[PDB]
Length: 529
RNA sequence: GCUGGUCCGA
RNA sequence: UUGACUAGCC
RNA sequence: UCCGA
Ligand SMILES: [Mg+2]
Image 1 (cartoon, chains in turn orange, yellow, purple, green):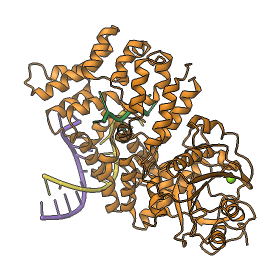
Image 2: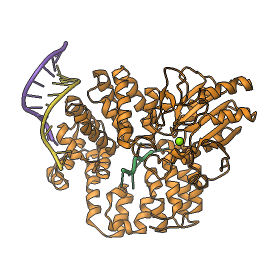
Image 3: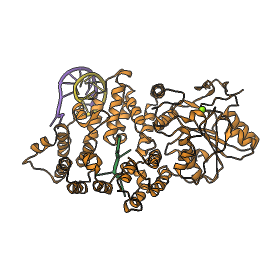
Image 4: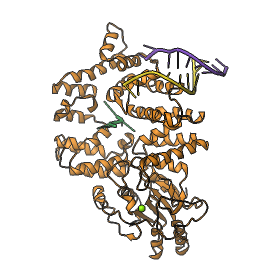
């Protein structure tokens, strides 16, 4: 009895034809939320992968778990546990469409909390448009009109003014489009002004409010909207700098000619929101606004390493990782990556995760480096082995008693250590992918060598394909031969529906890579909590 | 007063 | 933007 | 496709 044979009737064949278990639908939902389906996997094509997860979603709704789905989507969104928004928004769109009335109602109820910025709302609505044929249903019923109307009417006019000028339109939709389709009725004078600005433009608003009496709050909105117009009618460096300071305008408010100015950037740097700062490190370095040993460089490092703000702004470790890698590249533009910035990014990476108190148990961390793990993740340049290595570094730095190992169809030494800097672990890992997949190795190896481990964490895509015993079986053998209640945590690295964890074994757990809140689930499972 | 749906955006 | 239609609710 | 702590 080996992997090419089913262990029981509950097992199904994976992409290689070997037998594993079907991961639960709620668990597959989480994998989807964290990895999406873009780029598909080594075995499944993008489109097919998308349909598979969409199928699982519909199955959840059909099984009457639609409200649990929405709750899970909302939780991931609010806590920022997922690197990208597309998957959560696509899922919310499905739930808001054709689902049972309860599911649909919970979904729209979650719109304000899930769609925080215009880009989210625009993307959500576009997916509902794409789902319009496949789900045989229209989208502009009273519920969507109401949800969109509330999105605008429950917001402070001045804040909305910032939102509609910074994000005029994204992913196919503009605010004008939404107002036209929602037929919103402004809830106050500030909203009416903004609605008028979005629908007819500045000139219209100006003529509409001339000789008109306005509260002091409305006056603020008018002045702000005017500033966004004024900044586009001048090439004077100082006037722009003063408007930025005065109205806290951001990069999105400026013209191309303005972004060539080192001084405009320095003033832009003053109150640059966190994500924008992270993504423009390369640009500002090339322009010398982030000069070596400068005062800006030092300021930037302090912002990137402040755990409180990283959480507040919902900065995800994967964003940190991607930024780190491209910044280190030194080209995108050409620049000398600042070593202090590079060190701060490494530091922020770990801080971006939801940290927890250590358990003090013995962990054996095994990274799957088989050929399939060369698959790209989240449309980035980083493969699954690289991403999993980053997760291992996280766990290894949380649990002092951690041992890292690698494997394909044979055990291999791990070329990374707990003291390395992230960019270094990345370089040491993108040449390792090779060979077949034997997911039972870690447990078999530990037994053979008498290595004591309380927890086995295996980072893989669960596409095991060697004529060796089932990993579940290897785990059972380890428990008996070593006299240790070892547990296996399967850290999924894709959104396929396969798992080597035995559903009937309370000692085996399914979770997925780069869920910024995964360290919490691991701690609870480990401590039997 | 309210909430489901069809149409109306680009 | 500040709907049309339709189905229904208090 | 740039989440104002
Ligand atoms: Mg493989």
